Image (tube, rainbow over all chains, first blue to last red; front, side, top):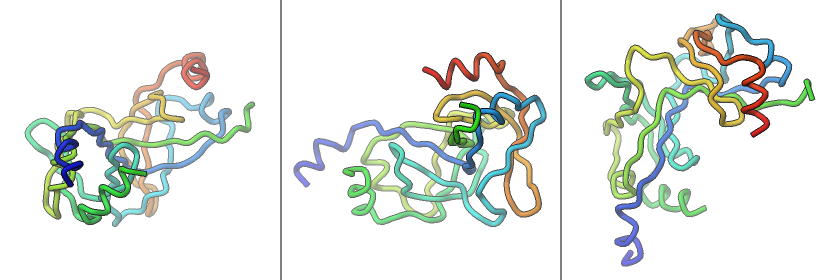
Length: 87
Length: 81
C-alpha cells in the first residue's frame, strides 16, 4: 500500500488479442499472401486485453480518432489485477 | 523440425500505460492502441511478427487473411532467434 505508492508510475505493456491458434513449422513456411488462419475466438466474444502477458480484461473494438482502441466490457477487480501482475 | 507446433497470436495492437491507470480502469474505460485504423492486424508466431492481415469470419470463428508476409527464409530466421 505504501509499497503500492512507489509502483503507480511504472509503465506496463498492454496487448489486445483477436485470438490464438497453433500450427506446424511446415504450415508457417508454406503460408502465402491470402492464406487464411482460423482462430480460437468465436463471433459474439470480446477481444482479450493482456497486461505484461496476463489476461485482466476483455472488450470490444472501437475507433478513437485515427487509431484502433478497445472499450472494456469485462475486467477483474483492482486487487486481482495486482495479484496477477505479481505472479 | 517441420512438425513442431508453434503458437500463433493475432494482435489488434499495443500500448503502454502506468500501473495506476491499469488499476483505475473500469467497465466502459477505453484503451487507445498504436495501430491505425487502415492497417492490417499483426500475426505473431512464437512472439515474432511475421505477417499482417485482415480479419475475416469463417462460419462462427474469427480468422485473418494474410496481406503482408516476410519470406519463408526470414520466417525461419526469426523463429530461430
